[PDB]
Amino acid sequence: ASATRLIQGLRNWASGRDLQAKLQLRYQEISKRTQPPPKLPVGPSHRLSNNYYCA
Amino acid sequence: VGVFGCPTTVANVETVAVSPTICRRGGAWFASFGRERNSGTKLFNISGHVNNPCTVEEEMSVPLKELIEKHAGGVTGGWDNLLAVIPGGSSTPLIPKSVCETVLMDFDALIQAQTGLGTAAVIVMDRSTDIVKAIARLIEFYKHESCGQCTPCREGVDWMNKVMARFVRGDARPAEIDSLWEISKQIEGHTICALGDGAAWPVQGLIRHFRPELEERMQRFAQQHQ
Ligand SMILES: Cc1cc2nc3c(=O)[nH]c(=O)nc-3n(C[C@H](O)[C@H](O)[C@H](O)COP(=O)(O)O)c2cc1C
Ligand code: SF4
Image (cartoon, rainbow over all chains, first blue to last red; front, top):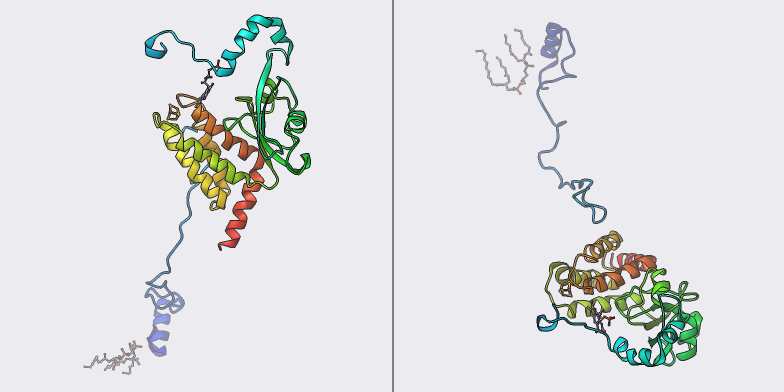
């Protein structure tokens, strides 16, 4: 992303595609390494009534 | 196999004491009172919130309103002050004021009211009564008086007393009402004697007749503690 515009233009000419829109090197746009604590949902049988195992 | 392994008949004081009167006075005389297959006289113990709590011998199929208004002078504050009646002692489920107007105090007409006759002990509970505190005290009676022999009573009656002690405060969510109902159905009929049945029945009666009062109890707990 720090490639100068002469090398950036030569590189786009040599590939034939627009390369800065689709860079295979990852930058600030990817997810944060430290994520907030989650709250996972419980299944359908987490009930206190009408929840017999035989049914 | 009864007492000492002998043949035995265990019989109530009332059904023993009335039998020489049946043999002297006659069988048709004792059969003339009350309805058919509900024959005879019966002792009734009207206690709770009445003006004159009293024991009285009365004919078998007497209406409940006539009994309470005549022999006990009516409910404290009149009949409009009535909230609920446990009809025959603690083992039977209670009936609300909407059922006590036309109900008859024998076996079969109370079985039609999805309760029982039992001991014919009319406990009257007026509008001034926290009914949830009374039924949780009743389940406290059934866990302090339970011999601990088999599993469902020994575990579930203490567990129903804990759930009812939270229902008094309202420290639950409403999905624990129906849960508690299932606990009663896991006790009623799966025990040795009918104290598991006699402890499952009042929980079922309280839920069936005052579910919205428990729900508004728990929701006002949930808003006043959060
Ligand atoms: C937990 C429990 C307690 C009982 N307590 C008495 C009691 O104190 N007095 C009584 O006459 N029957 C009591 N019974 C009912 C008896 O099981 C039985 O029905 C009765 O003593 C004798 O039957 P009878 O109605 O022909 O006299 C109790 C039943 C249970 C399940
Ligand atoms: S269920 Fe009956 S036999 Fe068992 S502990 Fe309770 S009262 Fe006793």
